[PDB]
Amino acid sequence: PSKFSKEQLRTFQMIHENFGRALSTYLSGRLRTFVDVEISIDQLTYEEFIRSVMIPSFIVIFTGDVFEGSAIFEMRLDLFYTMLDIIMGGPPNRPPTEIETSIMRKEVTNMLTLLAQAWSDFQYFIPSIENVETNPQFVQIVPPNEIVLLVTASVSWGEFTSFINVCWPFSLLEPLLEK
Image 1 (cartoon, rainbow, N blue to C red):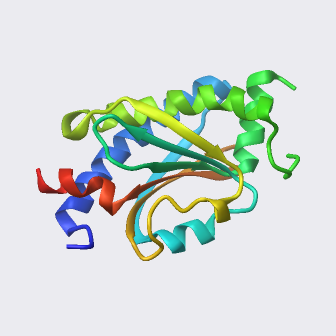
Image 2 (cartoon, one colour):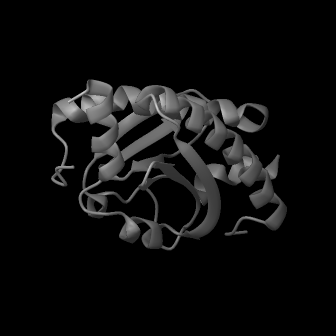
């Protein structure tokens, strides 16, 4: 089938809610302030997701040994620059420099690892960042009409609220969908 079943969605909801809790603790420690995270999932076409991403943005294309194909970890630039500023102790809306992406790549590797830990009992993997892009219109990892599981993490602290989205293409998740 081309779409995710109801029960399969619930499994992914629980997995990513675990991710959400680990992420909250992670970001709270990095930003040294209480950061709340609320997870919500949905399934839609890849086209819909990519068209919703701001230009520019911080798009991390990643994979895992145990997967075949890529997935996307996207972070809004307002969060990206706010996080970086705090970690560095130093937003600009323009696309990030190579230095800024390199510093934030380390943070993303940490967050992807937490994601993998949440996926432990179902399909544990070691994340590998394949590419980093700043323009969503240049990102077409799978066909437009293909369905994708979109995990949205609403990240907030104080009066700031932003997002981190993980896009899991149906084609990538198909085999685990089996067992």
